[PDB]
Image (cartoon, coloured by chain):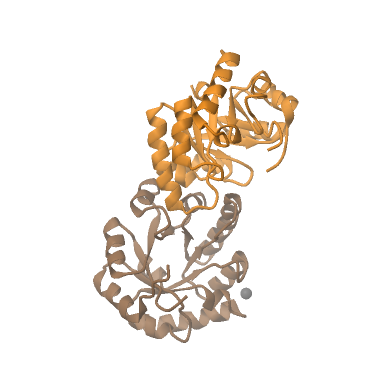
Chain colours: A brown, B orange
């Protein structure tokens, strides 16, 4: 279910590659979850791209999340929304969007446990490595994993050279941006990471 | 109902004045509707300000709208959302937020008729005068008024000097930004406009 489909979590970055093409390649390569993350674009544009990503993810039986924007997630029938300290409070998103899966970006053990208490469905725990400027490291990531019962996706500076050490901490998934989106060959970059995920998680 | 509460429609602009302070003064001055219009702030901030303006508007029995953001409108229990060409499509907004009043920003007769057809509850028809920079003029405003059955609020370049001529096109209300938010005394500017509105519309 959710826990399994969070294993390889790929986030868009139009600074690096256009969303639709890059998501297609990531999905070809074995991404199990996609997050649309668009910093500054009109709502209509977010909606149109979101509709396309919702179709592609469905074609590959992948989960689809939108960063921040609950309106957009609702409008495109996304599986969920990712929420951080500058976003809609968890309890409020839950009220207005009771069927969305809520991911919470957390940067400390206190924040992890609080997000879980407020009803987050999974955590994005970071930043594991330098990339909020807070860096939790492998040690901090491991402590969050040990303390919470909801799924935990590691994030922050994760790539093929460190993915194994990250996955050894007990997380359910890794989230990547640059490692995939900034690659010369997006699909191959994703395949390399998915192999490591399969190797460590089983 | 809606039609009577659209008569003096005041829109925020933090480029001129902060929202909470200025909305209090406009409500004191007789604004009947307030629209929160914030560019480039975090969702958390939009939510916090929205909650305050929701409370304020209720205290003065004024309607409360949010520009663009259906998520924010839902989260703060606003009365409605205003939607333009770069925003969520009307039909989609109605699907995800079936209890919100929908205002449509329209800049032509075709846009007016299409928005009404799609189920807009009222129109923001403009720009009447120079202040999306499209200008429709008094004749274009009148034509819209003659052609649609839903309430029409005029917008764009409106002030105490041209407000009567605008009101004589048959609109249900006037929307102002600079005339009130750019005034030295926000309350007094709003009082003046409200009087003009009451005197023409009766
Ligand atoms: Ni390909």
In the displayed structure, B70 sits above or below A73; it is: above
Q: Residue furthest bottom?
A: A161
What residue do we see at 52% from left, 67% from top?
Answer: A60
In the picture, residue B112 is in which quadrant?
A: top right
Q: Residue furthest front?
A: B184
Relative to B69, is A101 above or below? Answer: below
x then y, percent, for residue B65: 49, 36
Left or right, B90 with reference to B45:
right
| Ligand 1 - quadrant of the structure image | bottom right
Quarter occupied by the N terminus of chain A = bottom left
Q: Nearer the viewer, residue B83 or B118?
A: B83
Residue B170 lies, with reference to residue B97, above or below; the image says above
For image coordinates 43% across by 42% down, the residue present is B50
Looking at the picture, how far across and down is residue A86, in whole percent?
42, 57
* Residue A1 visible in rendering: no
Q: Name the residue: 73% across, 32% down.
A: B136
Q: Residue B78 appears at what percent x and percent y?
A: 44, 37
State the quadrant of the C terminus of chain A: bottom left
Q: In the displayed orientation, state which residue is furthest to the top.
A: B202
- Residue A66 seen in this snapshot: yes
Q: Nearer the viewer, residue A138 or B102?
A: A138
């Amino acid at each position: 279910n959710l826990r399994n489909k969070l294993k390889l979590y790929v986030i868009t970055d139009r600074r690096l590659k256009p969303e639709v093409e890059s998501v297609r390649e990531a999905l070809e390569g074995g991404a199990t979850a996609i997050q649309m993350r668009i910093k500054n674009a009109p709502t209509r544009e977010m909606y149109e791209i979101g509709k396309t990503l919702r179709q592609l993810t469905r074609e590959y039986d992948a989960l689809f999340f939108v960063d921040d924007r609950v309106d957009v997630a609702l409008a495109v029938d996304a599986d969920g929304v990712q929420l951080g300290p500058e976003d809609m409070p968890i309890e409020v998103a839950k009220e207005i969007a009771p069927n969305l899966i809520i991911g919470a970006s957390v940067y400390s053990l206190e924040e992890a446990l609080e997000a879980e208490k407020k009803g987050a469905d999974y955590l994005g725990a970071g930043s594991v490595f330098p990339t909020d400027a807070r860096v939790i490291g492998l040690e901090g990531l491991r402590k969050i994993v040990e303390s919470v019962k909801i799924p935990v996706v590691a994030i922050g500076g994760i790539n093929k050279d460190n993915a194994r050490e990250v996955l050894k901490t007990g997380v359910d998934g890794i989230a990547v941006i640059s490692a995939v989106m900034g690659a010369e060959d997006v699909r191959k970059a994703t395949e390399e990471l998915r192999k490591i995920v399969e190797e460590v998680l089983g």
